[PDB]
């Protein structure tokens, strides 16, 4: 039947001082086509592209997206890397060059066998209004807010089929 | 050859005002054994468990971990959920009840066919000190800091085999 509150807490330790400045900096997802991914995460979800890195020998690129004001992006190349890679809660999209012109290639979202990774989640002030806009923009849904058991919570899909939860922290609780 | 900087930025739209309060709140990973996972994320990496949710009908639990001072966590149940779910850069661990008793079961880390999700990444002040401690603790490495060509960057594995990048934002002005 899963862990009790007490038993779970007993598996938690205090934060060692060696970790006192650590931060959760990135989640990395592989994307078939950066052109579509960048459009979606910026235009649909309102993120900013804060940093792009290219690796000519290994034939890939990295794109870092985050909810930052673009005015806060350092102007100078090396400070920009340091500022971008020290932001909390970035999404790192990896583009293996060539995948966008490979009809036999696609990435797996982790929600069908074999499962692992499930989703990223965006907290929003208003799930319904967010998702009305998503519908208007042609976004694909796994779960509309009012579908299924858990009313008020939605899951959309990015261009690769990655699941993105859309949740309002303040309506969570006052539910089921 | 992937996108040029200029071409990539061309694909980026400014944020619609409706998204201006959005934030990247969680990354969800399924975990075979929440006891081991809680031990790893708290004692090894120095995260804090900020909320736990049990769903006896669906036979699963959720554990939200973050780099948050436990002394900031609200005492009242509703206020705690609203606070936890509004924190940036959380890790959501999903425990499907009974996986820890099933020798035939394991989750997939996204780093082999079928690929998708790659890793989460922790920004640390010093990759070499951090990794020295991980080694004293018997952490399983995927890439030690000096192995391979990307010197000064590391990968470890959590108890499910998910990869976790260890990066130093202030040295990383040498890579790209
Ligand atoms: C797949 O399950 C989830 C759920 C699922 C949780 C619920 O359905 C729920 C019901 C009442 C309430 O007051 C809060 C939540 C909630 C958040 C989340 O991030 C996640 O991954
Ligand atoms: C994709 O994540 C990155 C990468 C990318 C690095 C890798 O993908 C990698 C994977 C396995 C291995 O053994 C060595 C390297 C490089 C720099 C960076 O800052 C970052 O976040
Ligand atoms: Zn990375
Ligand atoms: Zn979630």
Image (spheres, coloured by chain):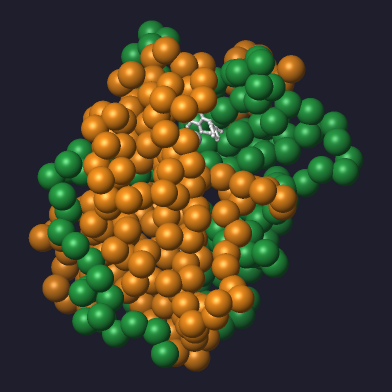
Chain colours: A green, B orange
Q: Quadrant of residue A36?
A: top right
* Along the viewing direction, whichever of B8 and A144 lies nearer the viewer: B8
Measured along the vertical axis of the image, is residue A60 above or below residue B94? above
- Image quadrant holding the C terminus of chain A, namely bottom left
Residue located at (27% from left, 37% from top): B132
Q: Residue B91 appears in which quarter of the rendering? A: bottom left
Above or below, A42 against B58 in this view is above
Q: Nearer the viewer, residue B145 or B172?
A: B145
Does the image show residue A71?
Answer: no
Q: Is residue B125 left or right of residue A104?
A: left
Residue B23 image point, x, y percent: 40, 47
- Residue situated furthest top in the rendering: A76
Residue A42 location (% of width, % of height): 56, 36
**Which quadrant would the N terminus of chain A be assigned to in this image?**
bottom left
Residue drawn 43% across the image and 60% down it: B159
The number of callouts visible is: 0
Residue displayed at 14% across by 73% down? B75
Vertical placement of residue A18 versus A85, above or below? below
Q: Residue at x 55, y 58 (%)?
A: A117
Does residue B52 appear anywhere in the picture?
yes
Residue A73, given in percent of the width and then of the height, sits at 38, 21
Residue sitting nearer the eye, B52 or B130: B130
Compared across the picture, whether B157 is left or right of A102 comes to left
Percent position of residue B56, x then y: 44, 90
């Amino acid at each position: 039947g899963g862990l009790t509150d007490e038993a779970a807490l007993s598996c938690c330790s205090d934060a060692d001082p060696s970790t006192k400045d650590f931060l959760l900096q990135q989640t990395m997802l592989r994307v078939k086509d950066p052109k579509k991914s960048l459009d979606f995460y910026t235009r649909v979800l309102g993120m900013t592209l804060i940093q792009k890195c290219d690796f000519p020998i290994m034939k890939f690129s990295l794109y870092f997206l985050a909810y930052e004001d673009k005015n806060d992006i350092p102007k100078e190349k090396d400070e920009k890397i340091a500022w971008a890679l020290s932001r909390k809660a970035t999404l790192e999209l990896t583009h293996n060059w060539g995948t966008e012109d490979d009809e036999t290639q696609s990435y797996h979202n982790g929600n069908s066998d074999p499962r692992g990774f499930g989703h990223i989640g965006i907290a929003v002030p208003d799930v319904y209004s967010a998702c009305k806009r998503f519908e208007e923009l042609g976004v694909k849904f796994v779960k509309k807010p009012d579908d299924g058991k858990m009313k008020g919570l939605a899951f959309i899909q990015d261009p690769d089929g990655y699941w993105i939860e859309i949740l309002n922290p303040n309506k969570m609780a006052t539910l089921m």
